């Protein structure tokens, strides 16, 4: 009697001043699901077509976000902009103007936290991505659809747009939505997944009618509702703080990776969104692949209000010369080096640590690497140029880069597990994985990376090393 | 310095409409003057142009309906950062 | 479920 999707986003233990904007097709605003909670702006910018059909997409999504019976955030107030015509087609320019309209509205008549849902996609667009970034930096939360072409989301916009929350779709079996050659987009530009198949919601067919629809937009609509609710509880959240919560509250490792192309399984977050039940937050950030130079370098960055606590690297062939943490524009960045040598990925661990400063100590595998007082070691990075004790980083000829943090209310512990293609070691419950690395052994390691709170080392003995922290 | 961009997915392109993006500090007054400059230089060449929208608030710049033939000229206008051909978006 | 109102699916059972 509770639709599968709404049950799925309800956490295992469970118990307004936010406005949600929708850029879509026309809306049937008097539908009983949403009547009185959606304000039609009458902003309209659509290309000519080449009636109940006209508002089916938009009405269903408004319902998923705020519908009385089938909505995620049942008490959410919405505002709609028309940027998609009756055939569900829009333009980049129309979307730019709509986004500009949202900003001007806000300057004229300021309200509270704003969530903008963008249930649409086109090809990669420099200008649309730039506009979204500027709107996000102005303090607005953007939630977008990953796209429906069973493709890398980085090739689409606004899905690839830095700072927007990009959402992919899973079904009742927590498997990625697929329909022949079509299905959910994936990859490193996707932040998480949410229910996106067989989603019951308002049908614009009749004022009380319901229909089941599927899409990365339906999935994005769940995240916008979760986001609206989270901002109601914590109106002061920054976009980075909202993203870290979405990730932290998500169900983890439930998607069967096999559905994605092989090279994309590492890059694709295995997260299905969920509401919070009524701290140190960390996330893993993958870079774009470095390319095949011998001097090629991949760079992974954190958000401005995030701290880079660790930095690891990964190459499928294994031909790599490690990684380093280095300051770029007054911000610690993660840099990975390719060996002679198809290329590498840089893998950052970005965390929300206030009452924290953090510094990098570059030294050889030097005996303690955070020599200071009350200072915790959060991560060990390592690089070399040839191709052939809680506070100390072990290595072989290699240069070490240690992330050292001053966080009086913070405790860290280092856990090792040594044994093969994959070795893992996980932090205990209540602990956050801040650093992940492998010790050099009688096996050539392809690299290491953090998957939620699990440290993964890939090799062709092998030992995984996880640094785990928590507040106290 | 000014660059041109068009959608990589060919069936999604909308030739004849361009988003002209100006350098970040450009004031709305400059965007309008740059757009009028384009129109005038275009007119001198026998081209009709239509300024559909002037942007301000997110990005400075404007939307222009014109022949692609004018891109080399428009790329030479003062304050221009990049120009992007309009393209389609779809309900997902 | 799949409706053609969402690009680019036709009418198909979903679930
Ligand atoms: Ca994103």
Image (tube, coloured by chain):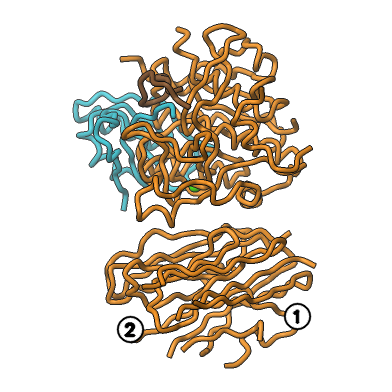
Residue B79: percent from left, percent from top: 39, 46
Give the mark nearer the N terminus: 2 vs 1: 1
Question: What's the colour of chain A in the image?
Answer: orange
Vertical comparison of A371 with B53: above or below: below
Give the residue displayed 49% in from the left and 20% down from the top. Answer: A57
Identity of the residue furthest to the bottom in this view? A366
Q: Is residue A296 visible?
A: yes
Q: Chain of mark 1?
A: A
- What residue sits 31% from the left and 69% below the top? A317
Task: Read off the chain for label 2.
Answer: A
Nearest the viewer among A135 and B20 is: A135
Q: Secondary structure under badge 2?
A: loop
Placement of the C terminus of chain A among the 4 image quadrants: bottom right
Asked if one can make out residue A46 in the rendered structure from this viewpoint, the answer is: no
Tell me which chain appears brown: C
- To the question of a shared chain for discs 2 and 1, the answer is yes
The label number, if any, that marks residue A374 in the structure image = 1
x, y percent for residue A167: 51, 40
Front residue (pair B1, A168): A168
Residue density around tag 2, few if under 14, some if 14–19, many if 20 or more, within 10 Å: few
Return the mark for residue A387: 2
Which numbered disc covers residue A169? none
Q: Quadrant of residue A274?
A: top right
Residue B85 vs A318, above or below: the answer is above
Q: Position of residue A3 (x, y in %)?
A: 62, 26
Chain seen in cyan: B
């Amino acid at each position: 009697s509770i639709p599968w999707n709404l049950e799925r986003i309800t956490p295992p233990r469970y118990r307004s001043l936010v406005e949600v904007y929708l850029l879509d097709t026309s809306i049937q605003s008097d539908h009983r699901e949403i009547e009185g909670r959606v304000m039609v702006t009458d902003f309209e910018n659509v290309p000519e077509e080449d009636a109940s059909k006209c508002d089916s997409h938009g009405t269903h999504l408004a319902g998923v976000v705020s519908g009385r019976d089938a909505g995620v955030a049942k008490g959410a107030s919405m505002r709609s902009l028309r940027v998609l015509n009756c055939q569900g087609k829009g333009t980049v320019s129309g979307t730019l103007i709509g986004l500009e309209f949202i900003r001007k509205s806000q300057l004229v008549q300021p309200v509270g936290p704003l969530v903008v849902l963008l249930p649409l996609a086109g090809g990669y667009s420099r200008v649309l991505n730039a506009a979204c970034q500027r709107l996000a930096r102005a303090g607005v939360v953007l939630v977008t659809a990953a796209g429906n072409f069973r493709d890398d989301a980085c090739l689409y916009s606004p899905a690839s747009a830095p700072e927007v929350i990009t959402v992919g779709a899973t079904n009742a079996q927590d498997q990625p939505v697929t329909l022949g050659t079509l299905g959910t987009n994936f990859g490193r530009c996707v932040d998480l997944f949410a229910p996106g198949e067989d989603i019951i919601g308002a049908s614009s067919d009749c004022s009380t009618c319901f229909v089941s629809q599927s899409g990365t937009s339906q999935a994005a609509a769940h995240v916008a509702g979760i986001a609206a609710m989270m901002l109601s509880a914590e109106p002061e959240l920054t976009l980075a703080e909202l993203r870290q919560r979405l990730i932290h509250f998500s169900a983890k490792d439930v998607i069967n990776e096999a559905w994605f192309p092989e090279d994309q399984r590492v890059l694709t977050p295995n997260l299905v969104a969920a509401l919070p039940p009524s701290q140190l937050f960390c996330r893993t950030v993958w870079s774009a692949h470095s390319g095949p130079t011998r001097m090629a370098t991949a760079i992974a960055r954190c958000a401005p209000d995030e701290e880079l606590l660790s930095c690891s690297s990964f190459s499928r062939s294994g031909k790599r010369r490690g990684e380093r943490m280095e300051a770029q524009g007054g911000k610690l960045v993660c840099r990975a080096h390719n060996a002679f040598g198809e290329g590498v990925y840089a893998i950052a661990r970005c965390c929300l640590l206030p009452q924290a400063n953090c510094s990098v100590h570059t030294a050889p595998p030097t005996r303690v690497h955070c020599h200071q007082q009350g200072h915790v070691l959060t991560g060990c990075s390592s690089h070399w140029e040839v191709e052939d004790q809680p506070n100390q980083c072990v290595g072989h000829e290699a240069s070490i880069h240690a992330s050292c943090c001053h966080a009086p209310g913070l405790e860290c512990k280092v856990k090792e597990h040594g044994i093969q293609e994959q070795v893992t070691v996980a932090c205990e419950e209540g602990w956050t994985l801040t650093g992940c690395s492998a010790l050099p052994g009688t096996s050539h390691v392809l690299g290491a990376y953090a998957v939620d709170n699990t440290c993964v080392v890939r090799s062709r003995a092998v030992t995984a090393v996880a640094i785990c922290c928590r507040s106290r | 310095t000014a660059t041109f961009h068009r959608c990589a997915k060919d069936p999604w392109r909308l030739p004849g409409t361009y988003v002209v993006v100006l350098k970040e500090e450009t004031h709305l007054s400059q965007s309008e003057r740059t757009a009028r400059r384009l129109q005038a230089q275009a007119a001198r060449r026998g081209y009709l142009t239509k300024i559909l929208h002037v942007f301000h608030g997110l990005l400075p710049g404007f939307l222009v309906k014109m022949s692609g033939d004018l891109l080399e000229l428009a790329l030479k206008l003062p304050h221009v950062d990049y120009i992007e051909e309009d393209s389609s978006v779809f309900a997902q | 479920x799949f409706v053609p109102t969402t690009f680019a699916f036709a009418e198909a059972p979903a679930x």
